[PDB]
Image (cartoon, rainbow over all chains, first blue to last red; front, side, top):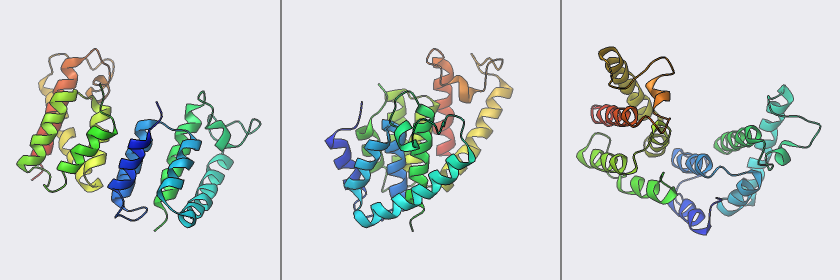
Length: 113
Length: 113
């Protein structure tokens, strides 16, 4: 049950005025992420739709650092012999990795301003 | 029939002008809750969506007060040998607990000011 075009259109329109990482944007994006239960691929699509290449790159770097610390510590469900967290989160049998990816994503995007 | 994006986005759209505790806010919240019959999970999602973190924290303080009072006084179908009302309202076969939690939710929201 992935999102459709209308959901993305509403998500972008409702937060057109606000700035990335504002409390309003964080509310709406967090609700979307917690409601649709998407993988990393869909999150990348959503970010490309919402913010430009500059904000995309900044979030990419911040999320790289956050994932770096998180999975360098060691995580309950992460096994580094199978692939990067971006790929484990895309397997529907690793929901723990998917939820960790979602939370790192939202925190990284909130850490912009 | 848990609410999708569109329902919650509407709810926030018409709960934007008014402030918590005002007649309009409570009217809309009570209608939504009485219609969709949401558990504690969906209620917490809706609250995080609507108002700032400060208002959510205030509401949860009031809700903890109400729930503690009710558990001391006694609930019709509350059995504390399995988990708190908080967790007993997530089981779909406990309608009484769920409706009681919804009513305490609405009361605690109405008593913020």
